[PDB]
Length: 116
Image (cartoon, rainbow, N blue to C red; front, side):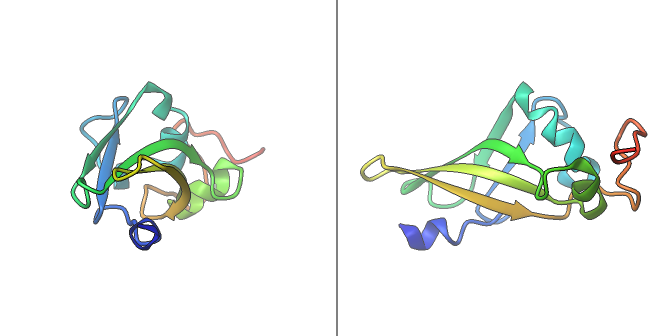
């Protein structure tokens, strides 16, 4: 089972989208928009190991703590709560993923400049 957990990847194993932005893909959302709006809801669509595994995204953290960096790289830190459907044991993993929207100055969707 740990084999599968350490092999969990996005867009391969499972996908997601926020209830805040339904009709938008990952490349259209700044790490700052997902960080401040997942509280509205996260919907998972698992395409692998759904007999053996359940994946849930419980939190989105900034790979570095601040939005400027996340936004410069189009990256995010996904806090995952993985359940083993054989003994229902609950596991956790921090999956760092990139490929999200990004601008070169880290500015956010609102035009606010990083820590300035």
